[PDB]
Image 1 (cartoon, rainbow, N blue to C red):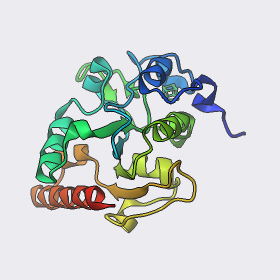
Image 2 (cartoon, rainbow, N blue to C red):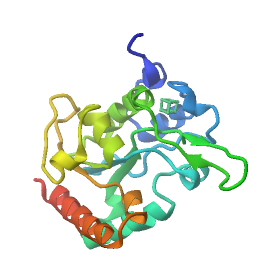
Image 3 (cartoon, protein in one colour):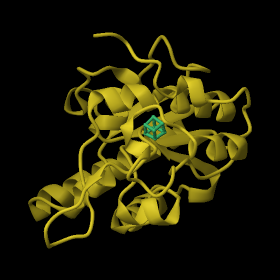
Image 4 (cartoon, rainbow, N blue to C red):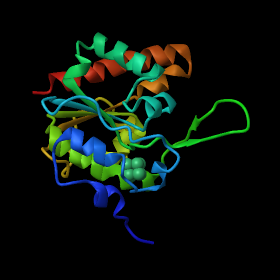
Length: 211
Ligand code: SF4
């Protein structure tokens, strides 16, 4: 096998977020563009100092064209308010920008499926473009896929959670904070979810206090 070009062929020579988001709908960097409605790019402006990265769009994100609009987005807004963070002062995006899903005989119309490492690596040039555009001071990695996208396939959020990290190789050398994805707070033991929500708030407060 070989290392793929992925999305790089499709990223234009621009740091403008609107031009990048329009170009991302034309991306064929992996197979996910085929069945998805549209690219789900980031939301926010280049003056943000804090960038947050999730895994991929969900069903409602794919329909709306923006990240974190489903129930996960409600929980994200709850956490952000608890951490004194204005959502529109952030740039929020996802490691993978087309909805990966399965249809099914019966049941839900579209069932989210985990992006493979190949798709995360293929879509990573868009992340690099976004970080070049926004020049964030701190990046919050919401969940295991977003964290692995910038920190390595073998990165474990449980090993480093809440730490303020630096990778050798991300534009602008922001501080990075790996934390829980808000969707994980929709399922699991109730008191573990409340503990993990508190910890998410802690990690967000830490990210916002990074100078
Ligand atoms: S997922 Fe990322 S890489 Fe695959 S097609 Fe959509 S934009 Fe291009």
